[PDB]
Length: 54
Length: 54
Image (tube, rainbow over all chains, first blue to last red; front, side):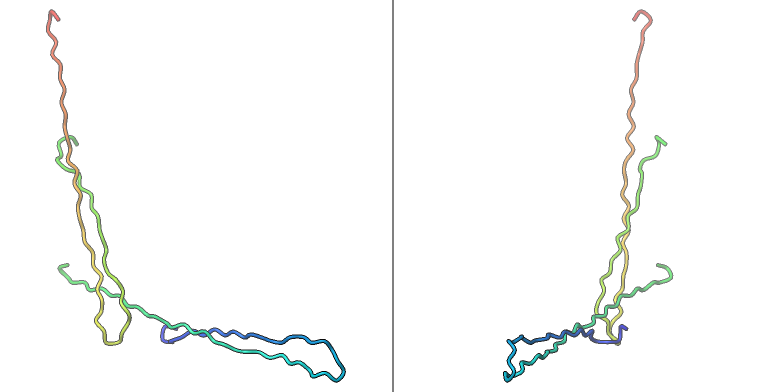
């Protein structure tokens, strides 16, 4: 909006590996991780000056 | 028109580079420059002379 300072984008990485089944074996677990990437806004200005005789 | 001396064509170069915006910063100014390129007209003459016996 030209007054804001940053633009944010997210990223999520899932994780988890399968295991051979067993009745009494421990249950393996899945999970996920989250990261964010930010970009800064740069604003520029330019102007002009005009006289009368000019 | 074969009697004029020059043919003139204009050229305009704008100028001005932006700067980062600031609330209390100096306003940058754009401008322009003008030049006029001239080409000279060249006249050439050729004649003939015929005699009676010739």
